[PDB]
Amino acid sequence: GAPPIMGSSVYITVELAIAVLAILGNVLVCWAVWLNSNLQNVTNYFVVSLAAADILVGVLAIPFAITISTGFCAACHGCLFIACFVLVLAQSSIFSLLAIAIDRYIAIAIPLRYNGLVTGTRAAGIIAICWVLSFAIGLTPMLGWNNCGQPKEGKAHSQGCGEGQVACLFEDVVPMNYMVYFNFFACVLVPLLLMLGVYLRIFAAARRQLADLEDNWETLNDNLKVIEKADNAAQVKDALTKMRAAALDAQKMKDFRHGFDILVGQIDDALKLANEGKVKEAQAAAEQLKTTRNAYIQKYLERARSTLQKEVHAAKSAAIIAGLFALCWLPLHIINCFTFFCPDCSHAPLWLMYLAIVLAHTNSVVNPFIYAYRIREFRQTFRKIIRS
Ligand SMILES: CC(C)CCC[C@@H](C)[C@H]1CC[C@H]2[C@H]3CC=C4C[C@@H](O)CC[C@]4(C)[C@@H]3CC[C@]12C
Ligand SMILES: CC(C)CCC[C@@H](C)[C@H]1CC[C@H]2[C@H]3CC=C4C[C@@H](O)CC[C@]4(C)[C@@H]3CC[C@]12C
Ligand SMILES: CC(C)CCC[C@@H](C)[C@H]1CC[C@H]2[C@H]3CC=C4C[C@@H](O)CC[C@]4(C)[C@@H]3CC[C@]12C
Ligand SMILES: CCCCCCCC/C=C\CCCCCCCC(=O)OC[C@H](O)CO
Ligand SMILES: Nc1nc(NCCc2ccc(O)cc2)nc2nc(-c3ccco3)nn12
Ligand SMILES: CCCCCCCC/C=C\CCCCCCCC(=O)O
Image 1 (cartoon, helix red, strand yellow):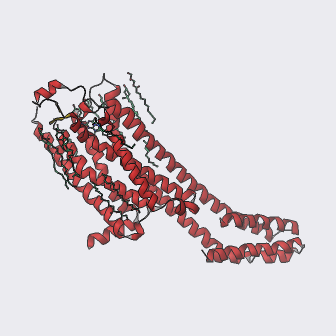
Image 2 (tube, protein in one colour; image 1 turned 180 degrees about the horizontal axis):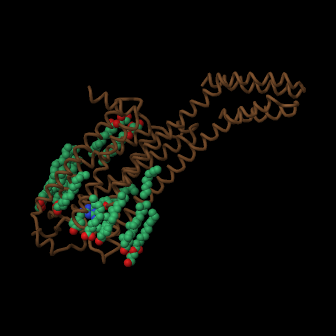
Image 3 (cartoon, rainbow, N blue to C red; image 1 turned 90 degrees about the vertical axis):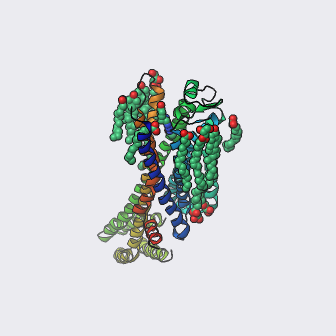
């Protein structure tokens, strides 16, 4: 048996390394948002919320993890706080991730109302509630759902703890049914599945809005080709009737309104010519539609197409952040599941336990790199602060 202090030294060094990067990179996220007013959205108030969570992983949770791993003697309820605080920060991150996803769904589904419905004063109120909830969920073991009432007292006498003290060890004070049923299933897993559903709807609503754009556009010019080589006023009538409905449908800030005002007006004129039975001047009236289409309607088709692609790109960035949360945190939860559901199994070896803790802490480093690579306003603000 190698002296514990040697493997301890690898663990502590790595933890300290991670804390440094967690703090630095996430202090940069918060500086960027404060400086650049382009970055002050309700979306970014939640990303600053989870940057705060990540900062406190490095300043508090990682120091707590280092000391919990020693088994130091302590009063059991003080042990519980050291051991559970990180669950507060984990829960806060889940709420922030959930909020961002809901915000990005509102953005894409009802852009009309978004600015009305979502505002930075209520966002701040939502964030405070979420932290309070996060202390409640994460510090529930201290309200009585703990193992303090039954100390492993042979382990306490071996390390020579004083009376009322335990050897502070996570799986000794925190019950595993809390961790698996209440923490993992209800408080982590259920919210993640909800996130998964929100993102599914977002990509669905963007995909079928693009289809509706391209449908209305193809409806516009096929009707035109029908008008073109028509026979009577009755068929010209139909293919402008389908154009105008498609115009009003596609319509749903000043040069855009012109473009359609001319378009439906041009249609409307060809319509009455058709009704009065003059076919070929109804045709001729309908092909300067072609002029308005090229000068106006397709710059609308294109910049609307350009904006949906930005919103999907922004929603895929947010999705990556949530996915990396799940990746970094699931192994620990899965190991607790084995520990709890299979008492016939050998406990996961100690080195794997610490690999899983280290991997969960690593999540506190990744997000700043995700912003810098994937959202240009963040990346250029990062550059501006760094060089200055
Ligand atoms: C705002 C920030 C800077 C303050 C951080 C407060 C932390 C470091 C404080 C608050 C509660 C503290 C202790 C709570 C009670 C106990 C039980 C005792 O037997 C050993 C010390 C121990 C385990 C704690 C030590 C650290 C402690 C956790
Ligand atoms: C990418 C992420 C989400 C998947 C992570 C899969 C990991 C966490 C899975 C894969 C294989 C797993 C277990 C394989 C079998 C053993 C031996 C058993 O006595 C304790 C659990 C233990 C030690 C494993 C626990 C963790 C386990 C390592
Ligand atoms: C990954 C997301 C989508 C769902 C999480 C699935 C979890 C709950 C699933 C995946 C693998 C599962 C089990 C793998 C095999 C065993 C050994 C058995 O003796 C007790 C159940 C146990 C220990 C697992 C229980 C929980 C289990 C870990
Ligand atoms: C805002 C920024 C401020 C930064 C804040 C720094 C965070 C505190 C660091 C580590 C806390 C862990 C300390 C707990 C270790 C206590 C050990 C102990 O209690 O020794 C008792 C002995 O074993 C017999 O009782
Ligand atoms: N099971 C567990 N253990 C620990 N630390 C104890 C690692 C260990 C496990 C067994 C042992 O005999 C000595 C040490 N931290 C832990 N953190 C979590 C956790 C936090 C959030 C989700 O899981 N689980 N967890
Ligand atoms: C920006 C400020 C960050 C504050 C971090 C403070 C650094 C402390 C580092 C690790 C503390 C580990 C304490 C060791 C536990 C006690 C040992 C024992 O009781 O046996």
